[PDB]
Image 1 (tube, rainbow, N blue to C red):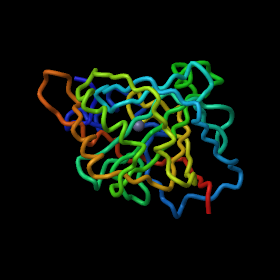
Image 2 (spheres, helix red, strand yellow; image 1 turned 90 degrees about the vertical axis):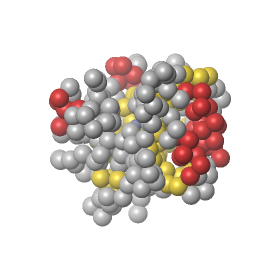
Image 3 (cartoon, rainbow, N blue to C red; image 1 turned 180 degrees about the horizontal axis):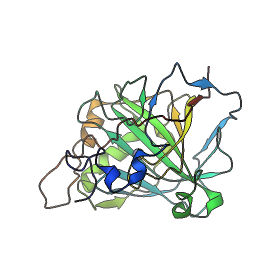
Image 4 (tube, rainbow, N blue to C red; image 1 turned 135 degrees about the vertical axis):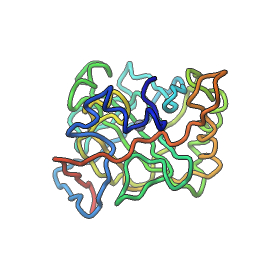
Length: 258
Ligand SMILES: [Zn+2]
């Protein structure tokens, strides 16, 4: 009986196994666009994914992760609020059972159909495991997804989901270009926060893009065909695997843009 997104083990229950769930810098949060202040101090954001090397995609019962080779300085995130270099290790989504919900962060309380999370770790800490133990160990790029026109660069991901339907399944996923999942503009909000799943460590600088990418209903429907359960178990569809907005507390959300 571990955490999950069910009525008896959902986000509201996580604090029992992870006290930090009621911490001072938990994520996600609602982004109040009118209160977020433009920060002249923010340097230009740099997303260098030209040499990104994906290797595999796995259903881990919480989402599916496209994993990358981070043994070398290739796909990195720098600039903006960040100091130093952060290396891409994996990306995953959260999505709902309906187009009206699914994102973890909200904008003026608005919930998007889904949210993409590109996870990077601060290279100054040597590895991901050590980085998550640091307040500035991680830097996650958040991108909202809305339903409309299909996203060409996402179809490759959608097509392999059939092979990793259940928890524990993984498949080769080489040569995937994450640049195809980025919106046109890099304008962003940013604030200090946490992982949004156990162990919910407060080691994350969050960079959430203002501009959503559009995906087709067909593409999102395939996300909804995945299973939380393992092979040969009662089917529990993988939907609504998002954590709700948490108290902002003593934090300020800064904007990179007008
Ligand atoms: Zn996430």
